[PDB]
Length: 78
Length: 80
Ligand SMILES: CCCCCCCCCCCCO[C@@H]1O[C@H](CO)[C@@H](O[C@H]2O[C@H](CO)[C@@H](O)[C@H](O)[C@H]2O)[C@H](O)[C@H]1O
Image (cartoon, rainbow over all chains, first blue to last red; front, top):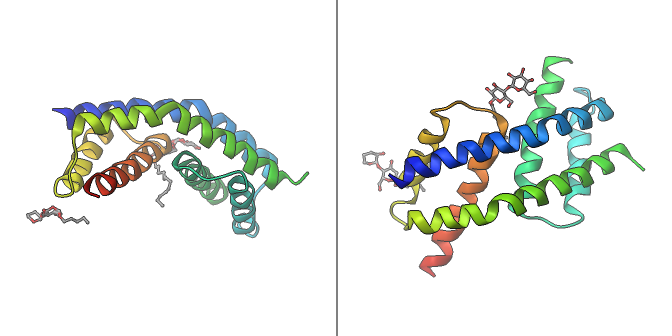
């Protein structure tokens, strides 16, 4: 069925995205040193800088992915 | 200058790369599915089920999110 085939290709695309960019997200978080106190400020300034050069679905979902990593990073620390 | 600005521009490159790498695949996948207004939600739920049968990470979720956007826009524009 095309549904299962599409799901399986999305899985490989997802894992490709994970592998390609997760270490880059790690490094960005290292440089940012976010805290619970500054996470919202940082996320909105990052988004502002991102969208200053345009918007497409790729940029939106990259921001959401990074924002989830940012929240989780702050959670697991402080 | 500011680290937040630099991170925003690095996400701009990443997002443009994700757009470049997979948008044609999403379009082909939508051509093969032939989704309509009435079956798109059930198509999306079965695809998501098929996707997460092999696990979950943030890359998989954002791929699904971006595909869902393309699916919705496709159905929308093609009924017009
Ligand atoms: C607005 C709509 C929502 C937008 C939110 C963005 C998408 C949300 C992502 C949900 C992902 C949850 O899925 C979860 O992914 C993370 C990160 O990949 C995986 O976690 C793994 O990678 C992280 C990355 O830092 C490591 O720290 C961790 O030790 C490891 O387990 C989990 O195994 C998986 O359970």
